[PDB]
Length: 96
Image (cartoon, rainbow, N blue to C red; front, side):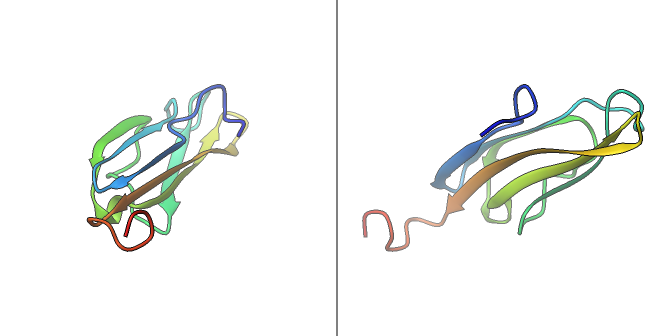
């Protein structure tokens, strides 16, 4: 439940149109971080920057988001699991 200070996001459970922030500080690994972004079985929005937001996530936007970020001790750090579930109009689990 413990993030790096504040996380990029924690979780959104919805039908497609979830609310996602992807966020770290960036350089080529000096102070701020150089990176590899992935999510929990799914592709992430473009990647490789520092701070990006997905205001409405579609089907390939469903999974859990995580990031491998290296800084100035040449050390790779991991930033938080942001879990977004974006369903089709709903399959028989919630109210059906």
